[PDB]
Length: 355
Ligand SMILES: [Ba+2]
Ligand SMILES: [Ba+2]
Ligand SMILES: [Ba+2]
Image (tube, rainbow, N blue to C red; front, side):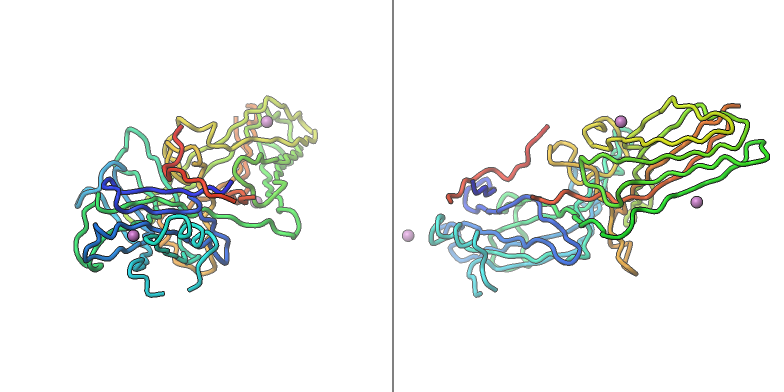
């Protein structure tokens, strides 16, 4: 049908409506945040209702929002006055919501700038609980007389939407191969060559690595280890670098001396196989089902890397275990993106599904 999400304040006087939880960041544009807020005039005797979208990097324990212990930096703020409206054309969905809700439904629309970072959440673990961080997008509606006075938290409604990063695939040639040649007490080297089928992968999509080994030595490769590793750099409040494997396959395959090897391995770097690992960047909260691995950060040409709170990157690693025991290895970069999203109105709680 036509799904619409809604959340109200504890008093039941202010309810926000949204057509989707996740808004897709295409490179050039991002989905508009078109919404409607239902007000109660008896509660708004003299006051107005504002809706503010805030993109903020946070640092510190997740369950705490207090001065001194929790750091936050606003990366983008936008304010609209939903009542009085004082009108930008409206969307089809907004017209339907006002048509159904009545005379006290008022619209609001945000246009997220493209260069802003996407929703990301780093879960550091039980040992270092204070190093948690991330950036979030919050839609907040509240009743006030202006944007300067202090507002009670339960007089307002907060909806943590996500911006997710999508990118189309490139029509150019296939990704280039990475090579390495190393000598292992040998007159001639061991040649390792790996490559990826695609450049841009999506969540839940497997990755095929093409491994090609030319062993011109007298040594024997005992094992072939293939893995996808996540790299995540914290750039705003406490500079840090994280290394975490999100997929692993130990192949017992053996490359003989003076022989040539070739094989295509496939691994599944899915969050469903990392529910116990920590120090890992996610695109949302570890509790929700719609949470996946953090998408690759799109670093634009000569762009401010610092105002993006966390930089996330992925690489496939291919390691050869030579018998003796040295190691020959190569890494392959790839981009992890969010999948393309592919009448009466039915309401539903905005709260994302747990477990
Ligand atoms: Ba009336
Ligand atoms: Ba190289
Ligand atoms: Ba497999």
